Length: 301
Ligand SMILES: Cc1nc2cnc(Nc3ccnc(N4CC[C@@](C)(C(N)=O)C4)n3)cc2n1C(C)C
View 1 (cartoon, rainbow, N blue to C red):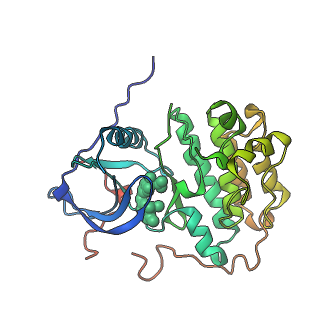
View 2: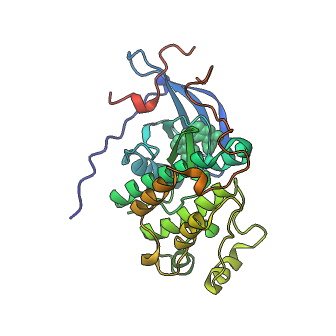
């Protein structure tokens, strides 16, 4: 029927890695900043360790996420580095030093220009088009689930809902009939773009989740962000059509945003644009430090 999933689930020893500090704590559990020094490899890989109370059902949920996360390999998608079989069960992931895009745009508004915004859109569309190739429906795309490796490199994450509720990011078919397609992820992509273009605003702020279904049914949509030209807003609007097949395809979104990213100032109007600066790996003290290699450069055992 379908193609066999030959992905390798890597089991890592507790002694092979160390927890440095806590990066975040939520519904899932706690994420730690860590270092992974494999076997006798003379490498130090900066990692993020996701950790869970212990219950059999919670372990199933974390192992389902590990399954999906180990099954992906794309420059714009977060891959699972391995798992550690403690009583708790820990997921070892790539350290994304700048955290989530949502908090990033909120904290750096005064230094984010049209080039970065448009490049981010291209990058998310690429990651999403890859998930579509792998026949994978995300079911939770949002600016909080896009992580920042460097200000110039972002990746899609959170496969806790990914298959083969976040109302304000969902397509109408999903809210009304629990239908989830790749075109339903396109609706979520539209909202994510709106979150970036507004510098991290909350979609439909003050409006309760039960009112959203009616609001969308009537024909109401998220407003035009002040920096958006009709060109960019038209794209957002198309991702929010009632007819799923009328919405753009991710491959088309790559093309559309790429054309626009070649002339950013023509599509986004930002006060003091281009005079803006963000940390680049060509900056002083951007990075013991000896033998530190990024996960993207550390391949196989
Ligand atoms: C503040 C912060 N700094 C981070 C550095 N690196 C990662 N690394 C990764 C890589 C892939 N996936 C994830 N996780 C974080 C928790 C997750 C379940 C989610 N909802 O974003 C996916 N973290 C996550 C980081 N965070 C989280 C808590 C948003």
